[PDB]
Image (cartoon, rainbow over all chains, first blue to last red; front, side, top):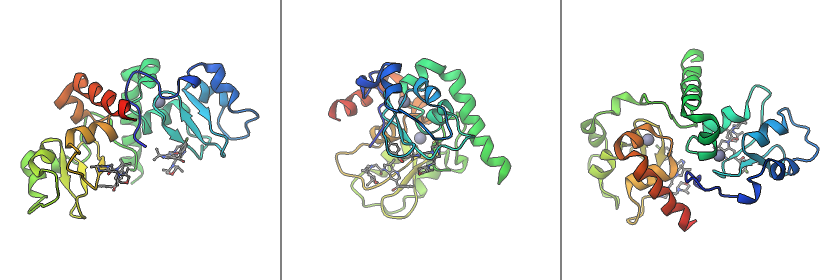
Length: 106
Length: 103
Ligand SMILES: C[C@@H]1CN(CC(=O)N2CC(C)(C)c3ncc([C@@H](O)c4ccc(F)cc4)cc32)[C@@H](CN2[C@H](C)COC[C@H]2C)CN1
Ligand SMILES: C[C@@H]1CN(CC(=O)N2CC(C)(C)c3ncc([C@@H](O)c4ccc(F)cc4)cc32)[C@@H](CN2[C@H](C)COC[C@H]2C)CN1
Ligand SMILES: [Zn+2]
Ligand SMILES: [Zn+2]
């Protein structure tokens, strides 16, 4: 249940962009499948459910406003694919953003 | 806010002092030590053995005697910046490899 924060991926079968792209197939949900594959995610085949090949972290119910890489950071901040690809400079923006997002509206 | 804080500012700054966090436990006779939990940034909710990190907001429960506060902090809230400040990524990584080698 806990997410992988090691530097080795949990599903190395899904480590190649093409392997991940194939899992979606015809994809009808609001959020783009190339965008999701680039962000590490492959598809389960149960609705819009996706999983990061590295952290194992899963997400669902994608709104059009929700960005793969942004959601990757929100829920799986320990991911090492995330850190390798966007780098803690970016990752900290999201979190301040996402915390500050909540203080305004309340 | 279900998602955990990975900013460098704590979520509950009222619980940022050790003496604050420890005062929440009171008489505590769950299996795992309350000073150990407070040092690891946890304070008590008062609903069983439920605790919360003052920084990440990350919550845990049902403490086995085998389960260590700092180890569980890393397992479930690896993005915590109190965790990173206090143990460093050197520690944090071995403890992940140790969990991920079990799983
Ligand atoms: C794109 C966003 C993602 N949000 C978060 C989300 O999807 N999370 C959060 C979290 C990490 C607690 C979580 N754990 C499990 C699932 C589960 O379904 C799943 C299991 C295995 C998989 F391989 C894929 C998915 C999902 C999931 C959405 C908000 N979420 C959802 C509606 C789930 O319920 C909580 C609520 C706050 C909005 N859209
Ligand atoms: C000491 C360990 C902790 N484990 C993990 C655990 O406590 N987690 C995992 C996680 C992060 C998904 C999670 N999210 C919510 C709670 C919730 O209760 C809570 C909310 C707010 C609080 F302020 C305090 C607690 C807890 C919790 C235990 C294993 N856990 C538990 C039994 C919870 O259910 C899942 C299962 C795998 C073993 N003991
Ligand atoms: Zn990941
Ligand atoms: Zn924490």
